[PDB]
Each structure stands twice: as C-alpha cells, then as structure tokens.
Amino acid sequence: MAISAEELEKILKKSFPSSVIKITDLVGDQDHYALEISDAQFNGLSLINQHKLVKNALSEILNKKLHSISIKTISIP
Image (cartoon, rainbow, N blue to C red):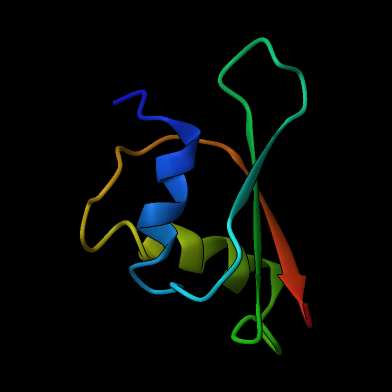
C-alpha cells in the first residue's frame, strides 16, 4: 500500500527481472506513476498484451495492490 516507486520494479522482476523498470512523474501531484519497461520479451506483442502482461505479472503473485497507472512499452534497448 503506497509502497515506494523504487519497489514497483521489484514486482515487475517476477516475470521480467532483466527488464529495465523506471518510474517518472508526469504531474507530480496525484498518484500518477509513469512505468517504463525495456527488454527483448515485449517484441511482437500488441499494446494490449504489453499493458496486460505487466498487470498479469502482479495479478498472479499479488505483490502490489491493484491500481491504475501509465505503462510505457520499450523494445530493443
């Protein structure tokens, strides 16, 4: 609950450990965290699959609570 943004990556590591997780502030006012994942596993997937995967990687282990945030997809680091 309200866990640090630096821990948000620890969760994405469950399925994407090598992946590069980074958070960025867009408004710096409300609970709006800009997630940035980079790896060679999100190649070929769709904007829906990439956005869903990140949610599934935490929907199985339930590492972090269920919230809504921006999830940017990056390939070929």
